[PDB]
Amino acid sequence: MEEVKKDVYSVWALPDEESEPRFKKLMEALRSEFTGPRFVPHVTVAVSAYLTADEAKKMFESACDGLKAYTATVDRVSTGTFFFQCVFLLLQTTPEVMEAGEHCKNHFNCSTTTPYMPHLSLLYAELTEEEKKNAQEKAYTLDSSLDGLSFRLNRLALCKTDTEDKTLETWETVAVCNLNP
Image 1: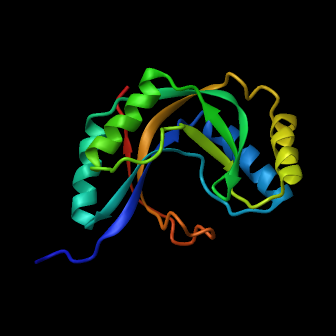
Image 2: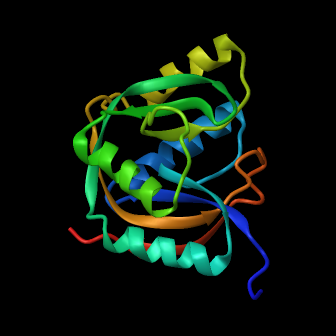
């Protein structure tokens, strides 16, 4: 037996250079008003089970090569019921967005989870319904043209994530890859 360390990895589709700063701007604004951890804009496409570094590397390369750059479209700013789904951008369930998720889950041999609800989280926090309703309005206030906004996902990031760590301290990006147009 060679590689004995194994970790759970998250795979993220990353916004293009053009849209990233619009997203960061809004994230930094909302977390400075509702207090939450700092993290990069991303659209999760898969969460693996336990993988050695070498296995994750291989799955990553396969995903990267067999996935073309695609785009996502903001439907609206929505809110959730727990820490990681506080205020997020709900994305249109287009074929390309749904398939990217399907194909990445195929490559990292993911198990059945919940329906794919593609989204780009804007804030991770535990707020009351009022504070939540307020953060949502604020997103719009800060960026009134979010609805219908389309952005390009041109990179994938391989991330070691303790999907339950609310500090995001265990969250680390291992590798990043450019998706072909």
